[PDB]
Length: 123
Image (cartoon, rainbow, N blue to C red; front, side, top):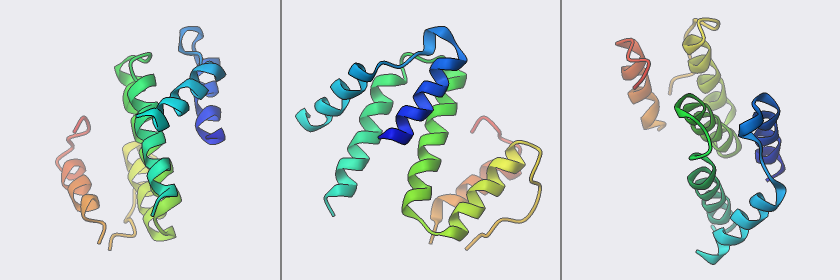
C-alpha cells in the first residue's frame, strides 16, 4: 500500500491534475473489502486501485501505471530470474538494455517476445 501511494504521489508531483488523495486511497481500500488469502486481498487491492484511478489519467499514463503495477506485483511474487527477464524486456523497450533475457513456466513471456520481435510496440 505504501509503495502504491509513493507511485501515486510521484504521479501527483509530476502533473498538477494527476494528484492523489489519502482519503481517496482509504475509501478505495475500504471498498475493496466492501465488494492463499492474503495474496487474494493484495490482488483485489491492485485490481481495484487500478479500476478506480485509471480514469483520472490519460492513455499514456494509463499504460505507465498498468505496466508498472504488473511489474511490481510480479517482482513481489516471482523469482529473481523472472525479475531480470522483466528488466531486460523494459530495457529493450527503452533502447537501453539490448540483450538476452533469463528466458525459461512463465508462458506469457514468450507471448511478450512474440509481440516485441515483430516490433509491435503498442501490443
